[PDB]
Length: 152
Ligand SMILES: [Cl-]
Ligand SMILES: [Cl-]
Ligand SMILES: [Cl-]
Ligand SMILES: [Mg+2]
Ligand SMILES: [Mg+2]
Ligand SMILES: [Mg+2]
Image (cartoon, rainbow, N blue to C red; front, side):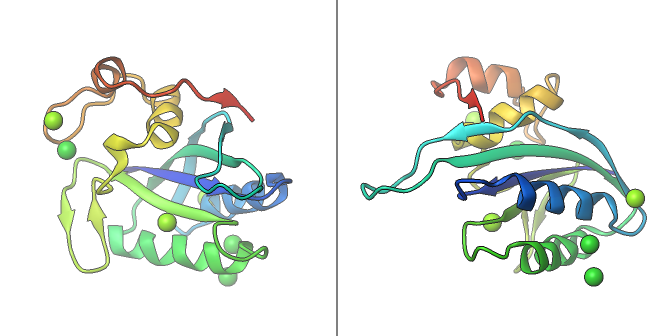
């Protein structure tokens, strides 16, 4: 089943952690990477001085159940997120065609249609994607205004 996972990091030199998280995703049992997006830059959300955020998206083929995949993403955050919090965020955006509303997991990710830093890398790797409700990703990006984010 093809899962789409968002990756974010707020480090000034995020590549080692991001790359380690990507390697780790590929090494999840019964899973492998399909496609890795470009890495995008987004500005911070508070007034104090801090680095920009890196954001990306990955297509991961997996035979695991969604909650199983969640457990691995949380494991990788703990193992590879050395810098603290926001230094490595892994979020399941979409999982096959499945709609999930459990305790631990909501799929499609509950805010992703509102977040350019999710949708732009996703569109790079899945330009023809259609959401469970029928909305085309391309349409969302052309009807909503989302700043075109630059390459990291
Ligand atoms: Cl690992
Ligand atoms: Cl491990
Ligand atoms: Cl939807
Ligand atoms: Mg593998
Ligand atoms: Mg998260
Ligand atoms: Mg709508």
